[PDB]
Image (cartoon, rainbow over all chains, first blue to last red):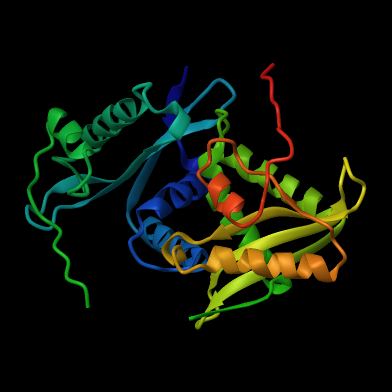
Length: 149
Length: 149
């Protein structure tokens, strides 16, 4: 059992959980020490400018079950207000309870209240979650292309 | 490609890598913040008792590739000096270069210098690592039995 509330006071815990989770997806042979510093840098960098909102899912003991990180910004193609989701993460043992879906609905509701015209997010092309988002009304508009150098 | 040296100077980096690695095997529904605090507590209490030795594998940029943590203690059945291996860990992208194998040889060599009569360690029962140790002269002497309450 859980509630979804503002997560401003949980940013440190969110940062640490994100660091733990994200490491398994890194494709370059960097040291964990190098990863930690870069993760810290990027996280603060993204957090430093703009209108951010965190929602957290908490249990009865106020422990962190998951979060969504939203940023209100301008669309680089449409030049309208949008809500960009940086991530949605759920603790491994709490997955299957519908918490991620609930956090997304909450984000979508907050976005509309703030006057956003779209929710926008990045999904890895190999990730089976693409279908999960499509079922929830998300459509791929663009590709992130990469070349190694 | 890599060297094996004393790892006293790398304890903080070892601790963080072990924190990252160990979290995958936690079978109880605890928060990551809870895990982190308990991991720190336990690491410190083990490090406080006995004679400890660390070896690290370092690449050309002096990045941590892996480590072994050795404790010289007494055997609870035979009452002879032994070296207990708390940990041997190699980073995911450095696996398959015999680094783990080399770290264990160094540990065995150091244990012998200290007058240990055995190397002892714990391996999880359905872990494929069981055969890896068996190949190197290790034999199962006892079982860690557990009952949930």
